[PDB]
């Protein structure tokens, strides 16, 4: 039966057929979702006349009794989605007044007569989607004074009369949704009849260029701001297409998923108030210097997947030409992901003088080499972020970035870079904060590799194969303010121990899968801000005393997947703030207190399973006792902590080891 938390009585997937009484009378909620109820007799609700929100979505309800509302005088949100209600009457919701949200989302209510919501002078959001409606008309007089969000998507409405919307004579609508209706015409004045219209959703309504043109006329001279037209048949645009919007202060426009092939010249010259524009998922063939004329106030532009695709046969690629964005002088964000553009041009980005975030992931096809001229079109953009993942880049040249003097994030991962870093690629990055090089072919380092980027703070070199790493002074030496150094899966041939000297601000160090055992001293020298340290998978099997001396800030240490067994007492003497310890899949035999006491003191989480535990009081008594009385999190205790010796204890669960009989 029903479970009852704070003031709410949840009875969701039980397959009920009756309304339960066991529940409190001090509840102001009641989730009867997803059951089997015939209907909701206006009498069985007395016990909880405190019901603030009755949620009976997804049942078999057929009719609603008028008395229900009055028997429940504090019903604010009623939900009857996906029920079986037939037709609403003039007398049904006649009592519900404190109502703020009514949802009749899925009841196949084909027709509406009279004024069924005359008294809902408080209803803030009405939902009548997915029925059989063929008219927007819900009344005869100016009613629903306070309505704010009318949802009527997924119906069968073919026309917007001026007559069938006047009941909103003075209703400040924030959102009218008519998505998924087969609109064949918009009569004159249809959208004017509303008090105020702010946001309109006409997705997936089968609109084409002409009907969209007549749509924008009917929108002239209304307070609309968000207009969404995604997923229609708007194959091309003219200057006349959006002209009717010059008489509006439109702000946001969605034009994705329309199969848009050709943006006419000046298709947007009457949108000087637009800030957000989406062109995602389309087939733009060309962008010319005239394409975005008029968008002098634009801020966010997404052209992700907005171009001509690959196609099965012909090698087709869009053609954006110099200056296409020369008018977007207030733009700060530009997403150009997932497209088949060949490369940049010496003036591709010119005019974007307020740009900050430029995304170019999986954007280019014919690049592969970056040169001193590739990004010259941004020499005048205050860029902070540059994404270049997935472009098949293989070489970066001297001075490539000298233009982006104000960059902070640089992302060159998932590429095929293959070269030696003389240090001159970064020439000019005065403010760079993070550089991402993970998932590349190979980088040959040098004494100067990062000499010109001292402001750096985060550097990732995962899965890259590093050459020339045992060189003094270390290649990481100039990075005094470095805080994250994630370089794993490189398997470095020789690691001189000078590495990492001077990284006083280092907080995270990732050195996994780098066969660190061979070269092995005292790696971690003065890294007293180290918090997270991962040395997983290095074939380690005899770790020195002193490598953790003075790392008082360690919160997690991961030495899993090595060959550790014998540990010198006091190694973890300084790790008393440790929250997490993982030595899983090692060769540990004993778990003594002179080694594991300190760290265990405050540990929130421990992972030490898959180890040849020796079941003898000398090896585990202290351990097994500690395990019984600690609040620490140990997972899979009962099954993945088994004893290995002696004979009689092969595979016996550690936690079951009797300790009483010990001394
Ligand atoms: C510039 O542009 C790049 C391209 O869009 C963008 O790349 C990525 O952006 C984010 C940030 O990493 C990724 O978001 C998520 O997916 C990543 C991998 O998750 C995997 O697993 C989930 C779960 O099954 C799948 O849904 C998913 O498809 C994938 O298989 C990953 O980044 C992240 O997941 C993980 O989070 C953990 C947090 O505790 C990590 O340990 C773990 O290592 C992993 O990061 C996240 O959920 C995008 O997937 C990725 N974009 C794509 C589509 O390739 C760059 O971030 C952006 N560059 C920057 C840094 O500005
Ligand atoms: C760019 O990348 C490398 C660095 O060049 C930069 O050095 C700065 C100190 C600064 O003066 C910048 O103006 C300059 O661009 C450079 O590396 C190779 O070429 C260097 C010549 O600049 C080589 O230096 C050596 O210099 C001695 C001096 O006489 C000379 O005899 C010797 O032959 C050699 O040239 C350096 O050894 C080179 N590094 C290696 C081995 O790769 C790149 O050439 C520059 N890129 C290009 C091709 O433009
Ligand atoms: C589009 O242009 C302006 C937008 O400016 C108005 O926007 C309002 C939402 C409000 O927050 C404020 O920014 C400003 O009132 C509208 O012009 C305004 O119209 C009102 C009433 O007619 C006047 O009293 C204002 O003075 C006037 N601003 C100016 C300086 O002309 C304009 O009405 C609007 N057009 C449409 C079709 O909505
Ligand atoms: C948009 O306008 C530009 C000019 O700003 C057009 O440029 C020329 O258009 C004519 C007519 O097709 C042809 O000469 C060339 O296609 C273009 N050459 C020159 C001189 O620039 C451009 O073609 C127009 N493109 C559209 C309709 O998207
Ligand atoms: C129009 O566009 C979006 C709706 O998703 C909203 O625009 C912006 O401001 C909102 C705050 O009112 C934020 O919640 C949005 O995240 C933000 N948009 C961006 C770029 O992410 C705005 O609410 C919408 N107007 C409506 C629906 O009335
Ligand atoms: C990249 O570096 C500069 C920046 O554009 C280019 O121009 C300089 O080098 C040229 C030799 O190729 C000289 O002819 C130019 O005069 C010189 N700039 C000056 C000082 O006026 C250079 O060509 C580019 N080199 C490459 C391709 O890496
Ligand atoms: C690395 O970190 C230090 C933080 O102390 C940076 O110094 C700061 O920034 C400027 C120097 O450009 C100083 O005038 C400020 O007083 C410092 N405080 C901060 C954080 O605002 C130092 O510059 C950084 N390394 C670089 C980029 O050289
Ligand atoms: C309402 O209460 C009466 C009490 O006799 C009960 O018989 C009836 O089944 C209840 N209604 C339903 C079907 O929930
Ligand atoms: C909107 O509210 C009522 C509708 O019943 C109307 O009489 C009134 O004139 C309108 N608001 C104004 C302008 O007073
Ligand atoms: C691990 O589980 C125990 C449950 O007894 C919990 O009390 C402890 O807080 C958990 N560890 C964490 C998340 O700190
Ligand atoms: C746990 O084991 C200890 C011995 O270390 C014993 O005293 C205690 O009763 C046990 N309690 C359980 C079953 O958790
Ligand atoms: C070459 C083109 O010529 C006209 O069409 C101008 O209106 C454009 O701005 C462009 O300069």
Image (cartoon, helix red, strand yellow):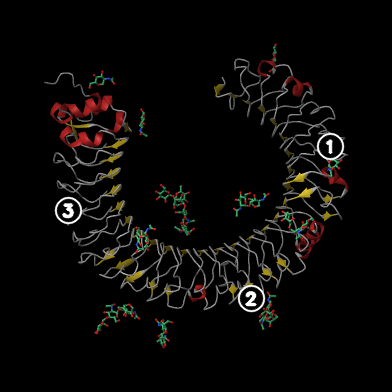
Which label's residue is closer to the chain start, 2 or 1? 1
- Tell me the crowding category of disc 1: few under 14, some 14 to 19, or many 20 or more residues within 10 angstroms, Cα based: some
Up-down: is 101 above or below 9?
A: below
Which label's residue is closer to the chain start, 3 or 1? 1
- Tell me the crowding category of disc 2: few under 14, some 14 to 19, or many 20 or more residues within 10 angstroms, Cα based: some
The secondary structure type at the circle numbered 2 is loop
Where in the figure is residue 97, as x and y percent of width and height?
76, 29
| Quarter-of-image position of residue 288 | bottom right
Where in the figure is residue 37, as x and y percent of width and height?
68, 23
**Residue tagged by mark 2?**
289
**Mark linked to residue 112:** 1
Could you say which is closer to the camera, residue 308 or residue 412? 412
Location of the N terminus by quadrant is: top right
Q: Can residue 340 be seen here?
A: yes
Up-down: is 317 above or below 124?
A: below
**Residue tagged by mark 3?**
522
Disc 2 from disc 1: Cα separation: 52 Å
């Amino acid at each position: 039966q029903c479970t009852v938390r704070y003031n709410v009585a949840d009875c969701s997937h039980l397959k009920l057929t009756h309304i339960p009484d066991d529940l409190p009378s001090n509840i102001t909620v009641l989730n009867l979702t997803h059951n089997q109820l015939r209907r909701l007799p206006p009498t069985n609700f007395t016990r909880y006349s405190q019901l603030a929100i009755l949620d009976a979505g997804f049942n078999s309800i057929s009719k609603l009794e008028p008395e229900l509302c009055q028997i429940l005088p504090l019903l604010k949100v009623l939900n009857l989605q996906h029920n079986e209600l037939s037709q609403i009457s003039d007398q049904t919701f006649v009592f519900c007044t404190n109502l703020t949200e009514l949802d009749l989302m899925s009841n196949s209510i084909h027709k509406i007569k009279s004024n069924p919501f005359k008294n809902q002078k408080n209803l803030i959001k009405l939902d009548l989607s997915h029925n059989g409606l063929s008219s927007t008309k819900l009344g005869t007089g100016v009613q629903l004074e306070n309505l704010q969000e009318l949802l009527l998507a997924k119906n069968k409405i073919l026309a917007l009369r001026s007559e069938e919307l006047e009941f909103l004579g003075n209703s400040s609508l924030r959102k009218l949704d008519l998505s998924s209706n087969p609109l064949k015409e918009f009569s004159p004045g249809c959208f004017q009849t509303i008090g105020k219209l702010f946001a309109l959703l006409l997705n997936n309504a089968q609109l084409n260029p002409h009907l969209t043109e007549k749509l924008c006329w009917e929108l002239s001279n209304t307070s609309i701001q968000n207009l969404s037209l995604a997923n229609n048949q708007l194959l091309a645009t003219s200057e006349s297409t959006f002209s009717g919007l010059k008489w509006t202060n439109l702000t946001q426009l969605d034009l994705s998923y329309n199969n848009l092939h050709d943006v006419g010249n000046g298709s947007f010259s009457y949108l000087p108030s637009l800030r957000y524009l989406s062109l995602e998922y389309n087939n733009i063939q060309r962008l010319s210097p005239r394409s975005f004329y008029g968008l002098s106030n634009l801020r966010y532009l997404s052209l992700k997947r907005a171009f001509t695709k690959q196609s099965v046969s012909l090698a087709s690629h869009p053609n954006i030409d110099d200056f296409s964005f020369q008018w977007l002088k207030y733009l700060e964000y530009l997403n150009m992901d997932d497209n088949n553009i060949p490369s940049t041009k010496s003036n591709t980005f010119t005019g974007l003088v307020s740009l900050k975030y430029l995304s170019l992931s999986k954007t280019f096809t014919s690049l592969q080499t970056l040169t001193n001229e590739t990004f010259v079109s941004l020499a005048h953009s205050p860029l902070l972020t540059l994404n270049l993942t997935k472009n098949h880049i293989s070489k970066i040249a001297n001075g490539t970035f000298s233009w982006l003097g104000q960059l902070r994030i640089l992302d060159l991962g998932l590429n095929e870079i293959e070269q030696k870093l003389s240090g001159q690629e970064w020439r000019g990055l005065r403010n760079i904060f993070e550089i991402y090089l993970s998932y590349n072919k190979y980088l040959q380092l040098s004494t100067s590799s990062f000499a010109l980027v001292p402001s750096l703070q985060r550097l990732m070199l995962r899965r890259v194969a590093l050459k020339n790493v045992d060189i003094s002074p270390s290649p990481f030496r100039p990075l005094r303010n470095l805080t994250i150094l994630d370089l794993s899966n490189n398997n470095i041939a020789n690691i001189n121990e000078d590495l990492l000297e001077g990284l006083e601000n280092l907080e995270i160090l990732d050195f996994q899968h780098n066969n660190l055992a061979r070269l092995w001293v005292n790696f971690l020298k003065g890294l007293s801000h180290l918090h997270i340290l991962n040395l997983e998978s290095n074939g380690l099997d005899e770790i020195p005393v002193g490598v953790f001396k003075n790392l008082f800030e360690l919160k997690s240490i991961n030495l899993g997947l090595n060959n550790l067994n014998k540990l010198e007492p006091f190694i973890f003497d300084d790790q008393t703030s440790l929250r997490s310890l993982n030595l899983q899949k090692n060769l540990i035999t004993s778990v003594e207190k002179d080694v594991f006491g300190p760290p265990f003191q405050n540990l929130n989480s421990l992972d030490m399973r898959f180890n040849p535990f020796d079941c003898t009081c000398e090896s585990i008594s202290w351990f097994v006792n500690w395990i019984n009385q600690t609040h620490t999190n140990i997972s899979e205790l009962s099954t993945h902590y088994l004893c290995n010796t002696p004979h009689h204890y092969y595979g016996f669960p550690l936690k079951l080891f009797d300790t009483s009989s010990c001394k």
